[PDB]
Amino acid sequence: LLNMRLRNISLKSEHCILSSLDFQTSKASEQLTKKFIYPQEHNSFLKLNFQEISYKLIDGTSQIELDPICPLKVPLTAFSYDSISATFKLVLLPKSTQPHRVKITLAYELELHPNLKLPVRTSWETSLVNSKLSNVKFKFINSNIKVIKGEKFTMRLQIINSSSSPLDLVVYYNNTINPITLENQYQLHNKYRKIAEGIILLSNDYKIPYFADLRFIGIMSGYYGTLSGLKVLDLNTNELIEVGNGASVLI
Amino acid sequence: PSMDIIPLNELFSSQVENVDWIEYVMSKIRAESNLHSRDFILLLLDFRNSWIDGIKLNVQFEDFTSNEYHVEASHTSRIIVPIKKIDYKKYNFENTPIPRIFPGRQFIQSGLNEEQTIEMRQKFWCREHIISKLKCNWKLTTDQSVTGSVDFNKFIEKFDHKMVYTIYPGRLFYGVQLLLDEPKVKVGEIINLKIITEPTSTCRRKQNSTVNFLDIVIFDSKTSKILPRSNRRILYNGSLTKPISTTKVSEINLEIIPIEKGRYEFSVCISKSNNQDGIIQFDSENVILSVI
Amino acid sequence: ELSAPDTRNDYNIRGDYIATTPALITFDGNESFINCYEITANNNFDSKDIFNLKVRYNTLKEQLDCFITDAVLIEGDVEWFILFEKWKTFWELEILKKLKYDYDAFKENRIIRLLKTSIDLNKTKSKIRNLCIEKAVLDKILICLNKVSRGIAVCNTDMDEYVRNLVPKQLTVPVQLPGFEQFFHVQFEQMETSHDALHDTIATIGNSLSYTVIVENLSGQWGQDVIDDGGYIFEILSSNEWLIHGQKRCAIKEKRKEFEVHLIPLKKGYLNFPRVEITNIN
């Protein structure tokens, strides 16, 4: 009851859940010690946090922070430190423990000594393109973020199919404007315009035959996150697989 | 088998001077300051052999000569050719294409209206322009003396509405450029702007509504245009509706003073009335400035 | 127009809108008319002066009524010699009940009347001594204006020096804040995802209350989100405030606050009170 603490956990896409703990001197404790300190004419407190650490599991391992941290001391403040946990594909929820050491130094070198230790579970409170029909999956083997200029470049698809008939699909980019509140109308027009002529495929209408190298050239500068022009058509039972993957900046 | 025509808007600064069209188009842009960018259109046509041996397939335009490609046996290889636009006011595209004979009556009650005839004349005479300069002069790699030419007349089939927009700007409704004084202006300064407007020969199509409404939109160079409250942004006198008229060389000159940042692009929009969904032309001249 | 008071500082209002070439506006609350003024601060701090404006205007009803009078029934001076110079006030009393359609007058039409009465107006003109040399013109003009539409051209040609412009005014006292601050921070982003190429905003805004605080929002990122945790070091210059954040994260919500209105305040150091918090993440 001197510094209220909370922990926030987020799930990054790079298979590393990041959990950040936040500490803040609570206002009720602030006024509680503040009137008794201002009786002796003190305006700013001094809670010296000298040893803050987090532990892992039933065997105690000290996972470090993401940056440096000295031994600080301040009043009426808040500070947050972020550790990087490991992403779990199973349903084993990791339970961690944190500990601090607040030295509540009253003045003229007459200090008290306080320590605290919480322990709880680091929950989070709740791409590979796959089709809807068959076993056919898509994933770009080369790193989906890429930094290019407006020059010629290459990109690499990959197909994991049912081995019964691996062939009979075609790719094409469809360089035409999709046929569409004037402000939202023109915003959707600018999205559909810079999609339809931003990059151009240097081999479209292209029969596939488990790799498939397909080659572009990029014209217009900008970050094309989930570049969604190219559209792999499946010949038999005529439907379309969108490929919402890959993101190329062109600067 | 197929063909498509796409324009370009980036300037293509150098060290990308290895790709065959880029040096020619940037050479024409580089000197001759009236020979500007933003109006070049690339045509994308795909050569595909049905043979057993490789070919070389050099493409000659009226002055553009491409590199030496290599199509092996059954593949496509999209050879990208630059071409400028064709000016509507300099030319005439509303005359009937002639027949060869003068003998037959040819069912002289022709079953066509006015506007269907005129769009048929446009669709024919645009490919009449783009065929009468295009060539190719091929050779086999393993035989080297079997060099022949090709035609294009039995290959290009027809156009659609997208090709006649992209090749011919006379199909559009207005012709606009922009004039800006200083593209590197400091923030405490107000700069006059200019929007020239020059209507088309498709102004005959409506003939009744003698006003159209030039909207103004503003977008951060990245994405996601700014709502017209324009705080932290361009501080602007007047309002962005600015009525213009048919058959007029009007100039809706405005003023613009920045607040925070640099990367701004300016463009227009034509909407034919003031209500929703009256829109006709999403005009896209889209010039840029900076504020340090 | 805009006018500067008698205190007479170096206020440089570069903004001054003159609608010389257009005699046109509309205020039907569909689009948004914004006027703006690029003023300057004084030679020192100056927080309470008085500004008064000058809007000339008209209303569009008597704009189209002036157009209809000057080019529908009194175009030439031949009819203006006799047929309307003896019944001008009667023409105004007839014109005041015209009630032209101002709902389709902003969409491809101008000077177009609504469905108002035109039957008993002929009987009302016939009741007085109105001669047929004017009763033909005053009926034919209303019959023409019952279904006609003009354009934006030849509107200023009727509006030119034929309208009393009510040059109204207002009062704008150029309101000010209370607690001046001057801070500058610096960041160093420990990258979770490599860089998301964020777009920046160096704010300048002051909080004006008592027992209050200054709350800041981080920069805006537009690539792959939820990441790029930015570390920071304060160097909170020229004051002694209270800080309430350390080594935040540039995702969905960070809100790196700074409790300001507690101790070590100052006066109005400028036109308003300021806090020119310029972060610099290099």
Image (tube, grey):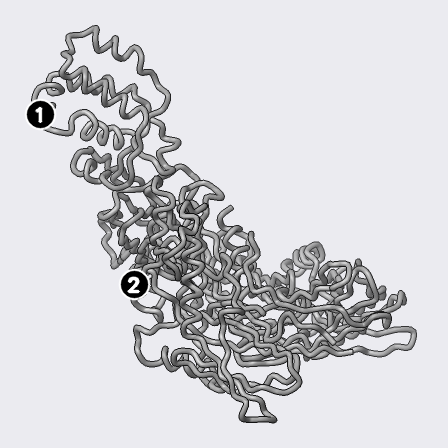
Circles 1 and 2 on the same chain: no
Q: In this view, does C94 lie above or below A232?
A: above
Q: Which secondary structure, mark 1? A: helix
Using the rendered image of the protein, determine whether residue C8 is visible from the camera's viewpoint. yes
Image coords of residue A205 (percent x, y): 64, 69
Q: In this view, does A139 lie above or below B17?
A: above
Q: Is residue B117 above or below residue B60?
A: above
Image coords of residue B259 (percent x, y): 40, 61
Q: Name the residue under label 2.
A: B90
Q: In which quarter of the image is residue A229?
A: bottom right
Q: Which secondary structure, mark 2? A: loop
Residue C78 disc label:
1
Question: Mark 1: which amino acid?
Answer: Val
Question: Mark 2: which amino acid?
Answer: Lys
Q: In which quarter of the image is residue B49?
A: bottom right
Image coords of residue C265 (percent x, y): 48, 60
- Residue drawn 91% across the image and 77% down it: A59
Quadrant the N terminus of chain A occupies: bottom right
- A241 vs B81, nearest the viewer: B81
Mark 1 — on which chain does it sit? C
Residue A197 disc label:
none
